[PDB]
Amino acid sequence: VSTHNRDKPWDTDDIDKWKIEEFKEEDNASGQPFAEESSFMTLFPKYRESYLKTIWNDVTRALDKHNIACVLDLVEGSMTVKTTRKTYDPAIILKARDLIKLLARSVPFPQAVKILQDDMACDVIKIGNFVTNKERFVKRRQRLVGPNGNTLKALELLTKCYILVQGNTVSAMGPFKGLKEVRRVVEDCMKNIHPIYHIKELMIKRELAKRPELANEDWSRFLPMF
RNA sequence: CCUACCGCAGUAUAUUCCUAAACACUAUGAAAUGACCCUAGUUGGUCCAUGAUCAUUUGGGUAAAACCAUACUGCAGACAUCU
């Protein structure tokens, strides 16, 4: 219970709080370019290089839709995004910082370019840090995909997120609730908890969410403890 | 006695119509709060009546010359007096 909360008369149920209104040039009410250049840089593994070398022009055109300048440096092994004078959206650089990172973690460009949309969010979760043994790490990482990918499919339908497992990372793209659930499932899966328990928990949560009378009270007696 | 090659000088190496593009000009309107470019100025840079930069199309112009190769045509086979 939070005490010392003041009343909020302006808050009513009519406002859709989660809608994202479009940002345009007229929305930037200062009317001036960004004061100084903002840049984000990442490194990528060496096996991605040639793929990046093929797709970079396409990547450039995508950022040309948002006035973001991109630089690939194969000698350094780095990808850089930066704002220009033509840039008017303050957030669109951060999404650019996501995109190259998604490109660094084996997410394909047609999937990764959707991070430029407003409703899309991404998470890159490190899985190589939990356990030091190689065989245990391989087994727990394969538990995420499962046999014939079905467990992975069971994740992607439940959290509504595109999930790609590569190396020491898992890259998830979707809504924020789905990202939260994916992070929980992945971090528990690296801690020797099988994903099927979380899958069953999400099923029970999904069926309880349909019933309106069950919203106020606790779901703990329905949920099997694991 | 005649042909062919050889010397020199010319002609041709696609033609007509429509059309696309380039370059430059020209016709009309727009000029000093002139116009354009650059993460952009403690005083930026470039072009600008010697016509910039924009719009309509106003209309015409240029895209050669020299040589090689092939064919054709023509002129000569000339040691050069002149006083």
Image: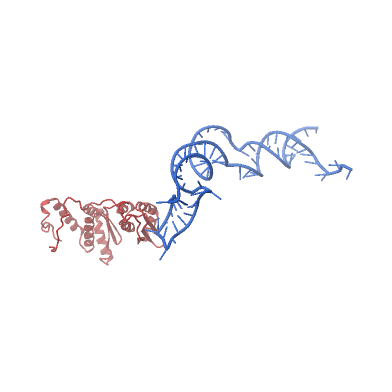
Q: Which chain is red?
A: A
User: Can the viewer see residue A135?
Assistant: yes
Q: Quadrant of the N terminus of chain A?
A: bottom left
Q: Nearer the viewer, residue A75 or B11?
A: B11
Q: Nearer the viewer, residue B81 or B25?
A: B25
**Relative image position of residue B61 (x, y in whole percent):** 56, 39
Figure quadrant of residue B81: top right
Q: Nearer the viewer, residue A189 or A34?
A: A34
Whether A1 is drawn above or below B66: the answer is below
User: Can the viewer see residue A74?
Assistant: no
**Relative image position of residue A80 (x, y in whole percent):** 37, 59
Figure quadrant of residue B68: top right
Q: Colour of chain B?
A: blue
Figure quadrant of residue A197: bottom left
**Relative image position of residue A160 (x, y in whole percent):** 23, 52
**Relative image position of residue A83 (x, y in whole percent):** 36, 57
